[PDB]
Amino acid sequence: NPKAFPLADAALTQQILDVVQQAANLRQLKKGANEATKTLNRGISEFIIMAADCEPIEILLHLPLLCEDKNVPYVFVPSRVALGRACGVSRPVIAASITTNDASAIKTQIYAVKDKIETLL
Amino acid sequence: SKTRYYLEQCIPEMDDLVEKGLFTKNEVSLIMKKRTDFEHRLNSRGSSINDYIKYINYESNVNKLRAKRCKRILQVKKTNSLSDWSIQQRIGFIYQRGTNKFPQDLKFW
Amino acid sequence: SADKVDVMIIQAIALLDDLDKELNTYAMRCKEWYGWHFPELAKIVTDSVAY
Amino acid sequence: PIEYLLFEEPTGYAVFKVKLQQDDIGSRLKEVQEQINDFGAFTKLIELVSFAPFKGAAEALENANDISEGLVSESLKAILDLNLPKASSKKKNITLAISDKNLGPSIKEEFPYVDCISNELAQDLIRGVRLHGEKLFKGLQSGDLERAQLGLGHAYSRAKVKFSVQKNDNHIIQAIALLDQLDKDINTFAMRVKEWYGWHFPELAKLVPDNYTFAKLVLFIKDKASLNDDSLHDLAAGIAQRVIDNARISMGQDISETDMENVCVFAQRVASLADYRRQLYDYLCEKMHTVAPNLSELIGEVIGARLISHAGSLTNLSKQAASTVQILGAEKKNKGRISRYLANKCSMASRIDNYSEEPSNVFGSVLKKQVEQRLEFY
Amino acid sequence: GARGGAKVVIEPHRHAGVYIARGKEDLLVTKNMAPGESVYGEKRISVEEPPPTKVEYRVWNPFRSKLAAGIMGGLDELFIAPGKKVLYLGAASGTSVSHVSDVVGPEGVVYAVEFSHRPGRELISMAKKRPNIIPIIEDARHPQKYRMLIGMVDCVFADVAQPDQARIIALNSHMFLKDQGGVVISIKANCIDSTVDAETVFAREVQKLREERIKPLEQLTLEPYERDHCIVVGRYMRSGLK
Amino acid sequence: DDNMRREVQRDLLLIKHRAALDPKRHYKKQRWEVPERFAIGTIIEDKSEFYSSR
């Protein structure tokens, strides 16, 4: 029973982070832990992703208490550098979020991802 | 009511208790009106174990008086009739009813 | 003389009032700090010196 | 066939004999399912025949955990072994109206001659005895149900969460909110010691301005009659000679006695308050080192206690974002970007030492080194 | 507007327990049970009363609490009176249960159930402060394993986020709710069914209630505060449904 | 109190005629009879808030 329990396996990892890159190219993503919690307690968040190998794990483990209280799915991913390459940014981002927007052309893939990870959790 | 039912069930003991001459009609009506008031107090709305205790005391003392008038008037101990076990049967009924209606007092138990 | 003086008996009840409100706020702080170990007695005793 | 019922209650286990039966076929009718609500007909239907209270608090928690996972325990098995008759195989086996199908097989495993039952008849009979509550038990108890179930609920919740009762930030909250108010109270009462001992020796507020050593030497010199003992004043406090000759040259003086004695009582008690402050500050220093060590090493102990007090709780501070750790006064262009850096590093340390199970100091130290390199960038 | 320091009158509302705080712009305000400490970071009115005493009040942020939006949109009657016992299916954290607690008051109780763990420890750390609530950290889908510690609540309320909403409230209300008692549920359309839209999923849920013997009597949509939720108020009839 | 202290006679008239206090608000129409039980409060701001509602 570790502290990063809903850790996604390989194929679900690849589909959630190509949805990440589509969102980053569609200007619908928030990069980083404190902007993630700011958009989370603002409310606009379809789902949030953390990285399960940051060198202190608690600096993004503070996000569960917000997200499963405000009823939004959350998923750990086994590589911060892969999530950085997904977000399309130089330094490794460890906590990304997808904002909510019904004027974005990845709504179908976002909802498929969200249904898969609610079944995962 | 049911107080009428209990009082009417205790009539044959006074019936043979006057049929044998050890209790005449005046004093048996006296003990019957006293038992009437005691039994309505027992089957009131919100009675008490003190009322159960003193009604039991009345029945034990009328049993002692019945045995005394039996050994004085008829000069026999056991009258082999309904008049002997009836008061102890009633005391058993009163103790069973008290332990049903008030089960938390170990003094009465 | 200065043994039948009044400028100390003014500040004596000034001290009594300040000490009264200080004892009240210390009662509140001790009641909640011990209540974090034991909440069920701040409602059952009220006399703070007995507390 | 419902003739015995088992009810579980946060003071004890109850077992009820079912005197007569409920109407089974018409058990959705209004004139039947109002009889469960009213009291004058429910005691026609259910009487109490056994009530054994578990008396230990921890044994109540253990019975509640064994029921909540659906398993028999010592007190439940004890009262069923007592009350449930051996229905011999010529007649039948006895029936028992219990509340849940998860519990059912675990009493059927242990007692063979019992037979559990929970249809909607057992459901609404248990609902009726739950509704009427205390008025069925006719006084076979000592203690009401709601306070006992409050305690049992809090204990069952903490035993399910396995909540760490060593991560205690409320201690640091009350510690610093007592500490600053206690410094203010020591200062005010020491001003009262000064203003009350002025009538006996008004050239002492000039010489001895420190409140604690003022109160301690007021405890030392009672009346202006010392005049000789110079070798105790450097202990209790050069200026020894100034206060000694000012004990005879000044004579702005009232000669009063009982008020001087109560000044002495007041002064020694204010000195006791100063000793209490000087130990409580050290207490919350080491309790800040124990509870919140990374934030302690990064920002300092009393600044950390002030910051957790401003946040309200350590968990609330952690679930705050890293840009809303703006607090005025604490975390004291080139004078502002260093404070922003220290702010979100303080939020990072807060996240570490709150969401850890019990924290370490190595991340506080490398955070200190990172922010010191960012300061030496200037 | 409504900054910290203005003077606001505190008028009483129809639903006893809550109050309207009328300043130059209005607020919805409940009378705080444990004074001195906000629980999820809301602003507090603080009135003085005459031995000088000082009692405080909390605002009720409807964008972050469910039934506050229903109260401000205007419901005919709730069942959360200042004496009742209130069950709370899907108590997330203190952020609404503290408001339902101090609406209920010092006599009645609020049994707040919760399935997750980290909101559970937050709920317990809030629950030590005020005494009229009972935190339970059990799944709302199994009302036979916290049947030990509660009994005969007087109104249930529901915010759970599962597509067996009606089965959850039906099982918890059969096991605990008394007859002629209230049930206030809060359906989230996009949560429980994403395919078909809001009014169809609301009608399907309220049909499931009136099959499970809750006679519904109010439906509110709370549109300017949250999107496409609904508050459905009902009685639990069990005897004389029609 | 029955004498009404005149300050909560001023500001109750103020919030009763609140609709003409600033020409960008437009409160919805309501009669607002004066409540015969009412207090006067003071908004304690949040400690984690500054520069925007203090």
Image: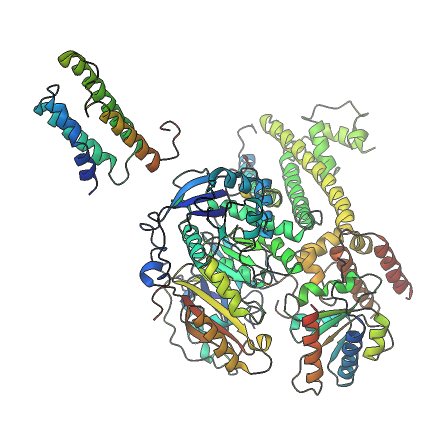
Work out which quarter of the rendered image holds the N terminus of chain E and state it. bottom right
Give me the residue at 79% from left, 29% from top.
Answer: D233
Q: Which of the 4 image quadrants contains residue B100?
A: top left
Q: Position of residue E187 (x, y in %)?
A: 53, 73
Residue D38's place in the image compared with E59, above or below, is above
Q: Nearer the viewer, residue D195 or B36?
A: B36
Residue D200's place in the image compared with E169, above or below, is above
Q: Nearer the viewer, residue E42 or D124?
A: D124
The reply, left or right, for residue F18 in relation to residue D369 is: left
The reply, left or right, for residue C46 in relation to residue A108 is: left
Q: Is residue D98 visible?
A: no
Q: Is residue E103 visible?
A: yes
Q: Position of residue E221 (x, y in %)?
A: 49, 77
Q: Nearer the viewer, residue E92 or E107?
A: E92
Q: Which of the 4 image quadrants contains residue A39?
A: bottom right
Q: Position of residue E116 (x, y in %)?
A: 64, 61
Give me the residue at 73% from left, 82% from top.
Answer: A28
Q: Looking at the image, which residue sits at the far front?
A: D90
Work out which quarter of the rendered image holds the C terminus of chain E and state it. bottom left
Figure colour scheme: rainbow
Q: How many marks?
A: 0
Q: Position of residue D153 (x, y in %)?
A: 56, 50
Q: Which of the 4 image quadrants contains residue B25?
A: top left
Residue D49's place in the image compared with E215, above or below, is above
Residue A20's place in the image compared with D287, above or below, is below
Give me the residue at 74% from left, 42% from top.
Answer: D283
Q: Nearer the viewer, residue D198 or A120?
A: A120
